[PDB]
Length: 49
Length: 49
Length: 48
Ligand SMILES: *[C@@H]1O[C@H](CO)[C@@H](O[C@@H]2O[C@H](CO)[C@@H](O[C@@H]3O[C@H](CO)[C@@H](O)[C@H](O)[C@@H]3O)[C@H](O)[C@H]2NC(C)=O)[C@H](O)[C@H]1NC(C)=O
Image (cartoon, rainbow over all chains, first blue to last red; front, side):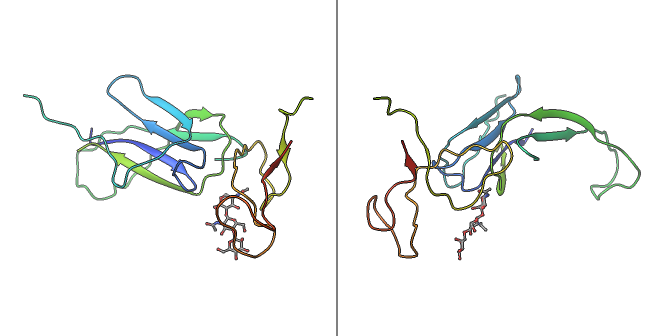
């Protein structure tokens, strides 16, 4: 489960409506909201023995 | 994405051969329909690390 | 005085069927550059 989700928009920074899939191990959630994003954002996971 | 609707078709298949693009035939079932409505021009993906 | 109802006055291009827009940037009605908030040929995107 390396890949998690997707984003959709026209400019993707705090000024246009944007769509977001994130698929966690639990129930997936879809949102359509305004958003601001980081330069290289992701959901870095950590191994737990 | 057509006239205020976002349609996603999905399929999960098992493969046990080379990483290259497989041959053979398989169809995609309709997964979900989203009634949102938005201009879309770009997209990007997210992965866990 | 009911002044809470607004709509759009100039737009770059026509919308699509069932498409929503909440833009608030000032429209450059003229070809001159428009910065900040207020100026000539660029005053306001919406009207009440
Ligand atoms: C959905 O979003 C896209 C992305 O912005 C919109 O395309 C944009 O359309 C405008 C209108 O023509 C383009 O503006 C043009 O800019 C050039 C300079 O680059 C200028 O010479 C023209 O006179 C005009 O002002 C803009 O470039 C274009 N964006 C692109 C191609 O990335 C599209 O119109 C939107 N759809 C709706 C229904 O609003």
